[PDB]
Each structure stands twice: as structure tokens, then as C-alpha cells.
Image 1 (cartoon, rainbow, N blue to C red):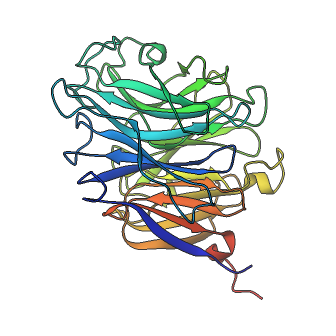
Image 2: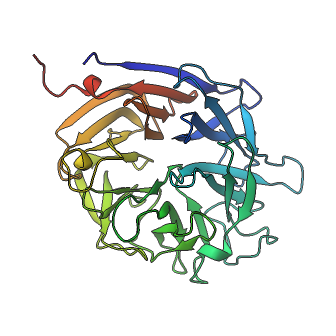
Length: 361
């Protein structure tokens, strides 16, 4: 077809009320609206910065965006409070939308103490905002206690981006959002937080690996769940693991040399989310990240046609500065990409023809 690639800034540092914007999350509502979420950062810092979770909406497929609205408002005056690092998750079965994010007071990720009391200012809490009206209004919950089965887990935060809902197997319908936790020994591990009752209750699976960080999951053509993680041990590559269950546990973690990474967030999605199990279309994956091993630059999109075994196709979308990026499949068959060019947050839209591969006809 005719390749397509366009982009436009949704937030630029210093404009619209905040000196700094970071951390993208993107999704499509059941109605077809596009939602972009990110941090508004009064002091240009991660938690415990008194950050706010912001959102912009598009009702015309991404061409035009409405005004910036506040999902969770941070508090800059004592008692200081902050909300950061959003991740959207849409229950396609019920139409409910969730926005996961940090709730900080005195401590950030590294300084969080063990404990689960929402009133304790020394712990980094896990919050979830739920909307049943397409992202218009939100109800909030601190779920730290629900997702801390091991009293030794002293800190955690949802990986910003977008979570998933399983379509196949015995756990079809399950909502999965990835988190990074710090255990008693001080190791960074990955863990899936999930719900089998459409968001009523959330629970944690078994933690995996060491030297883990922000991580994402995708459902493969056979129902297996692939975990793709930032490596806090800085190997120069992404770490991967797979789950064959529900009541999540993953196998051993290994470095994937096909995916160079400078220790930064990335996104991995199903190109055809609705394809039947085992079909050719169900094996197609798209991955976005900074391909440079020395800096956050050279943003590229890679495509796999074999459940992530090989990535034969790749194209650079941003030769320069490029930190976090998230992908979502749009209703018109194209793909949305929210990323950080260094100036705030930018939205891009591309199609498969743009990726190229063969110089046909």
C-alpha cells in the first residue's frame, strides 16, 4: 500500500502548565477514541517529585487532540504527594479502562520501605484509576496491600506503557499489568499483576529474574506469555522470559542479542490482536525501542513474524534522541506510537507498508 508516517507533539516542556513532561502511555477506548497519558513534572524528576498524571484524547483517529486533563493531581505543598509513570489497560470484554501509576509521598522507588499502609509516607504505593465512561471520570484505589504477597517486597512500580488482556486459553479475559519490585536482598525483579474478575481484585504472580526493570508482556500465537524487560544490569540488550501459565510464573531469563538496548523502556505488541490462535497473523509482533547501546537514540520499530524468534524487518523512526516509547494497534489497521523526543511527548502514526521489507513490486 502507500506507506504512512506522520507525527505531532502532544506536550512540550514549558507549555500548558508544566516545565517538563515525560513517560508515555497510549491506548484506544472501546468507542475508538485514542487516549495519551503522561507525567506533568513540576520539578522535572521521577517520584517523589510531586507529579501529576495527565491525559489527552483524540476522537478523530489521532489527527486532532483535545485539552490536557488531569487524571491524578500531585500536591506541591506539604504534605507533598506525587503520581507518576502511567500504564493504560483496557478490558475489551467489559469496556473498562484502567490507568496504573505510582503514588508517592516521601520516598521514590529506591527509598521505599517495606509496608503496605496507604497512610505510611515512606512507602511507594501502587495506585490504579478505573473509568467506566471511556476515560472521562475516574475512581481511585491504592492496591499495594493486594499485590504484595511477600512482606519482603519493599518497593514496586507499574511499568509505564500499556498492559494486555489475554484472548486465548484457560485464562482468556485475564488482565495483565507488569511491575518491577525490589525484594528483601535489594534485587530488582519483574512480576505480573493480574485480575481474573475484570479489575475487581488484583493479585501478583511469582517474581522473576535479577537485574530486571520496566518490563512488558505479550500473548503469543499459542497463548504463551512473552516477557520482555529492560536490563538494570546493563548488558546492552533486552532480557526475555516466557510463561506457560495463569497464576503467573516465568521460566529462566536470558539476554536477547537481536534486541540491543541502552537500558531504557520499550514496547512490544501483537500486530493483529484479534487473530485466531495459531494463525500466521497471530505470530506477528512489533517492538519499539532505542536501538543504540550507548545512548537513548535511534528509535526503531522491529517486526517479527514468528512469535518473536527472529526480527527480520526494522526501520528507524527517530534517528536522534528517543527515550521511552509505547505502541498500540489502531482500529483503522495502522499503529499509534507515543514517544519521548527529549522535548516532551510526541505521537506518531505509521502503517506496515512504511516498515517496508521488500522493495516491491
